[PDB]
Image (tube, rainbow over all chains, first blue to last red; front, top):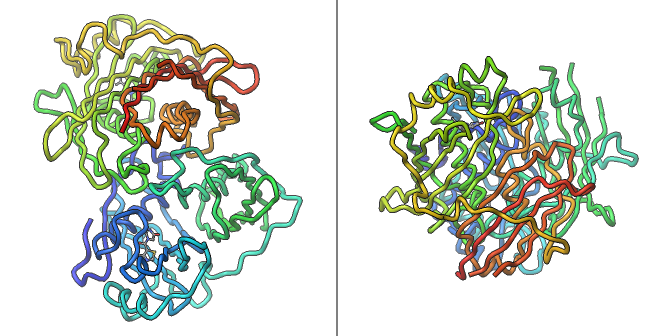
Length: 269
Length: 268
Ligand SMILES: Cc1ncsc1C(=O)N1CCNC(=O)C1
Ligand SMILES: Cc1ncsc1C(=O)N1CCNC(=O)C1
């Protein structure tokens, strides 16, 4: 991988692995999400961020602050097959005091065509108190160093799916998968549950017949609260709709505390 | 990746990923096991095996046969850190009518030193009846085309750890993790639970304090029966001792054994 000529974005190629594919012999959405996270991490290292798994700036370390995901939105047109080379371009942008955004474009390395796109919103959090906060002036000035100054969006459109409000699923759910627990392979190097695991848990309550007959086209996931290593999760899904749409909810199995909410759009194979 | 000059082994380089590492910022044993499986699949594709996830020969397809894992043994001296390049060399060998073996050597790409080694035993199974079989004359002939004819072993030593008999853990277990279930990311392209998932489930019953203070040096795992997509597993562990453990994976309900194994850990 490497930064582009202007030093304002980063590109990396990946060869899709045997264990990274599903029944259709193409990359799962979890493999796509792991690759987005990997290229994001390589971009951060290349522009001088912390090499400790937290990707913080100098001002962030002085104030004991970290970036936490608020939303992930992924749209896939073609999933790369086992053995194909996918090229992913990524860049960051500051959104005033709200937070920051990381965007991605996925391409077929051979044809050069765009096969997918993604966007993620990140918010500032104090590492100690776990309280969300606004982005300060000094942090906004550090982002100018490596971010394009004219707006560059993976999802530019006037009314795009990436910015839609997601409602809270009402009981009873149409489908459910209960008692989901993370194992050590679900944790990152800092022992927090990997953001990609929440995607897999959301999808666990989609009926197998939908997965067997449809391709996942869009997924939008809101991150409300973290699942801990010793927490147990319930994944709930209700149909909201040639195209199938679902509303999703992840909550703690005990008290029912919400951890994530989201939506998926599937098209017939 | 590519076959070596003699066409009897295969080499591939991997850059260790951010999500592939543990708290020590080095590759987990599950990442090592996934990389062994990946280079194994690339080797099979390059020597003309089926490209459907089963890696069968032409006589295996006519007889409706597939290879199933009987044992996996991995010994790691140094786990590669996040961003390091690891080089893995793999080859196969026929063991008469018993089955076949796939062996691996892991090296630090920069220094050229051996940082680990692995060996796996595979047995023939009829895909329809699920009955184990011996390897027939015709499939032993096909293995001669891409396997070294003089013995090449990752664990050559007589009476080594990779060939030891593993006992069955007796209740009560000292430690346990119950109610483990596979999700879709645990399945392979043919919807069977990935062999690497069983390694993770074995390790789930090791106390966190052992993981925090020790490095895993050796793991030997026997595969007895497959966990299905709708099965629930209990992982049991008892200390037998350097720290050594005896492990058992069994179905949550009736207690049917699926795997048994051992691990050896060294103080950090
Ligand atoms: C530079 C940056 N700005 C907003 S997100 C982000 C980033 O690259 N990451 C990936 C690693 N860990 C994180 O928490 C965030
Ligand atoms: C060629 C060969 N011979 C014994 S094991 C093996 C092998 O490469 N694999 C990896 C893919 N799927 C399998 O079932 C076994």
